[PDB]
Amino acid sequence: MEILYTGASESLHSTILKALLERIDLGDTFISDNYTRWQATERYYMMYKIPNKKDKAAIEKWNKGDTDFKSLVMPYSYAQLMTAHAYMVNVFLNRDPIFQTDSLNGDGTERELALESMLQYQVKAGEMEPSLLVWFMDALRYGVGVLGDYWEEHVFHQTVFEVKKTRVVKGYEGCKTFNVMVYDFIPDPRVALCKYQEGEFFGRRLDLNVLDLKKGAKFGKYFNVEHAEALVAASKEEMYRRDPSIGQQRSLKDSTMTPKGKQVGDISCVEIFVRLVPKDWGLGDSEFPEMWVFTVADKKYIVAAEPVNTLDDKFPFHILECEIDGYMNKSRGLLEISAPMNDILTWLFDSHMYNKRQIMNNQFIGDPSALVVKDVESKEPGKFIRLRPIISQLPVTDVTAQNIQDVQVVERNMQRIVGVNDDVAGQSSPSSRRSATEFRGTTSFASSRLANLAYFFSVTGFRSLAKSLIVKTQQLYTVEMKVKVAGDNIKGAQSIIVKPEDISGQFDIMPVDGTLPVDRMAQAQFWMQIMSMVAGNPVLGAEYRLGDIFSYTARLAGLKGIDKMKIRILDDDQILALILA
Amino acid sequence: IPNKKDKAAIEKWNKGDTDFKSLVMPYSYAQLMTAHAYMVNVFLNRDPIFQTDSLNGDGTERELALESMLQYQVKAGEMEPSLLVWFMDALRYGVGVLGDYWEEHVFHQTVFEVKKTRVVKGYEGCKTFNVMVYDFIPDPRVALCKYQEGEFFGRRLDLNVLDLKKGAKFGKYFNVEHAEALVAASKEEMYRRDPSIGQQRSLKDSTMTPKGKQVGDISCVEIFVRLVPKDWGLGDSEFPEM
Amino acid sequence: PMNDILTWLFDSHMYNKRQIMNNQFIGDPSALVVKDVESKEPGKFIRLRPIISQLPVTDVTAQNIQDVQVVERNMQRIVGVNDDVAGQSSPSSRRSATEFRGTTSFASSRLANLAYFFSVTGFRSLAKSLIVKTQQLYTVEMKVKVAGDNIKGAQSIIVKPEDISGQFDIMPVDGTLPVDRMAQAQFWMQIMSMVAGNPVLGAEYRLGDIFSYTARLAGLKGIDKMKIRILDDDQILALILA
Amino acid sequence: PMNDILTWLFDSHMYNKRQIMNNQFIGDPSALVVKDVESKEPGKFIRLR
């Protein structure tokens, strides 16, 4: 539907605008509540310390060529954040499938490969893993990770310039994920963040280039641009302090006068997904809840509003939390937990340098009445100063030389609170089994919380990303394009055609994480033994065909060419035709 | 609780100098989480969760089908986050509570080709909802060790007016009419000053919705009782009923 | 309480250290040239004889480490997470007289007993509720979907109405006593291998169904379709004869 | 009974450590400058012997 701004107090436009601004105002309360805490997290990451009084002079000494102390903070706490993130990367990101699946009934077993090939291509060509890296990191730094996905259809125009001709490139189509800032997303206050799905509305901020908006105007997904294009103005309110230069804000030195035309810049916008009853909202006739995606430009205009056609009811958004309480809480990140103990870690060191600063110097005590003076002030291999030994040496002792023992115990206590390398005895000898022999790899052990935390991440959000990814890639792709990308892996039609209700129900397939890895090498070996003994006792060879088994095993092992090595070598469009009915 | 010297320490920290802040040893806090990690590794870290065996052998053939059904249902029902919230509660409060129910998810959607509306079958399967420890109502007479032998079990919950009224057409709700206007209720036992931020929301903020309706939630209580219909008056029988 | 003793002990230590440990001097300023003492340079000669003295400071609470160790050991005694009263001895576990994962990551840590207790009290109840609900409320029209092809025949899926209530021919098991079907597949495989010889054994049983059942049990779940016939889908509902 | 001996001893030990162990000083305040003793800094010179 289309809504057109006109001045009327009563317009679908004015009423929808007022209601959506009321929703956004309610949502911003939760973000405003949590601002400061999150901000502090940043300061610790950067280990920013307020300079001391003694510090300025010291900096000056250096300029003049002299050496002195500068205040620092112990990075011991900073070490666990990054080591824990390195551990997380290995579990999920740096492995081959990255996203991998399994089927229960086995109807799915057939479709399993094609679907993994599609996911592999899509994740590899969508530049998803940089977004992923941030997601894991953000969650760890602050305590909440946010990631959202959307469908991308990239088409652009180009000139060959032979006789001044313009060509259209199809471009890339596939799911793309955009990482969300931790101060722009708007949750629903009433529901705890964890059960975000249940709530009425999820919002986030974004800015749209006027060039992109004009390009999308012809696409039919935008309207009221003819009047909204004149804004080219907005304001940003919540900014963190240490990380960016104030120059990050260019004082809105944005927009660059186009020759022979306007200027090109950006307009602030807010996305909101809502569940609604069209009648009440006035959009349509029906008495049942539905989900629609309105888009609000700044606080005055609406540019796009359309229904939702994807089958899954869930919002296309994914949240991770570090804490495991699971009820309403304020999530706590590792840095905030270790901050007090890090304070003790920093002090002590500091006190120790400062007392060593003030006390430790070689000096003498003596009465200058008797010594010759000129001579004491000289360095040579041997001199005889005159008169008896009146000079004395200063006895100086450092009381705080014992601080090492305190440093060790406080570091051990920080290990106790955070758990990165806490000692649990190393008797974790058995890998165990998941009972199928084809479902285990890289066992390790609990590693205390490190593994357990992982499990938490997997169930809470990674699965969601996948369920969303699999349902979207199984729904929106068309067979005319499904024959592409997934080539030569469609041995039969049953591996592609999916019933419209089947994908909604999620019946014959399910995604699995790398926490329980799937090792198809031993599966290939077991299949190979099965075929080897099926060769004998020709009743077994009468019940099954062998060539298809061999081809399936070869493809599963990763060869992916055997099908191409047959005498016949059928492929290409033959495959689209191959769909029977 | 902060010490008297802690105020001066925090003030000097605002000035930037270094001093002490009072803490507490997390040694006790360590065993809780390590024990929960062990619990997860034993129970919830393996995919099967539930395994099945038979004695007759008639159920031996049913074994594979039944385990496949349980595996699909537990994997698609998002049960394991509820399990994590469960074991932890037991180890935190000493009592863990978890309840299950049957879910039939159906929803409406618009294709918007010629303004058509389609109905999606959705997902059907068991789902478990975790219960907070100050909201569930047991039966005083019977100990929690054999709670199942008790008489009644209760717990609190809130229902969205959008959900309720929708379910009104489902036939499982009535008297929705007089009930709907109330959108205001109280919370008797909020927890520690520490976790929740005072009130995350000051009052039960419902959003004004134009054209003469209101969206929000209404407090509700669920109760399971065993009763004699002839005594209670609902019906004709002498034997107890659930 | 044991955690609290820890907090006092540590705290007293830091607090006493804060108050006293500092490098300071004692001396009579009548004789020393003041300007000189303040300055810091590699070599200085303050003037006159050594009147200055160093403060002797000793920390009495430097011995608190021994007390901290014993109180942590006592907390291990009370909670039992890594208590060594359990001691060291070889696992040697043959809990079940058959192929049921004998041996453990840990034979008993006294953590295990607790687990086992959680299993018996709540996890078996949850499994029973899940199995009875999923065996009752599902309809055959939908039971044919979800698990497909593992339903070899109607003997596998239909269940008498009273049979599910009585819980006769099936029972759930926990992962405390895991079930390892890999060795079961191997033992079945040996059984079939020797059944091949002595053709009376092959006269008493059929071999193809045994091979299919072993392959499905091993987790392949695709042999039903590898076969030449490849029957599936609706055929399965039809494959009923009430 | 043996548990009773196990409990005592510990208790006696904390209680005597409660009463005795604190860092304190002995001195005559007639000669010291007073204001100075009551301060913490990297280096100070209190006056007198």
Image: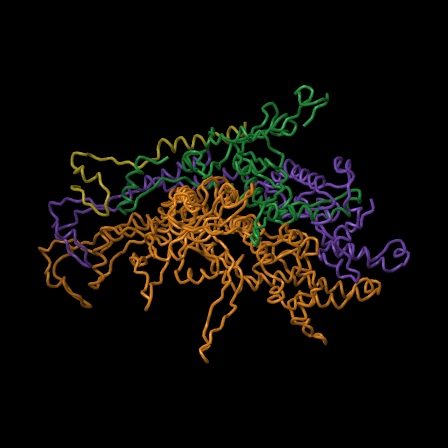
Instruction: Residue A394: give x, y in percent of width and height.
Output: 21, 52
Instruction: Residue A487: give x, y in percent of width and height.
Output: 63, 68
Q: Which residue occupies the foreground of this view, A176 or B210?
A: B210
Chain letter corresponding to the colour green: B
Chain letter corresponding to the colour orange: A
Drawn colour of chain D?
yellow
- Residue B53, visible in the rendered structure: yes
Residue C163 in which image quadrant: top right
Instruction: Residue C225: give x, y in percent of width and height.
Output: 75, 59
Q: Is residue B76 left or right of residue B181?
A: right
Q: Is residue B108 above or below residue A548?
A: above
Q: Residue furthest bottom?
A: A162
Q: Is the N terminus of chain B in the top left, top right, bottom left or bottom right quadrant?
A: top left
Chain letter corresponding to the colour purple: C
Q: Which residue occupies the foreground of this view, A6 or A54?
A: A6
Q: Is the C terminus of chain B in the top left, top right, bottom left or bottom right quadrant?
A: top right
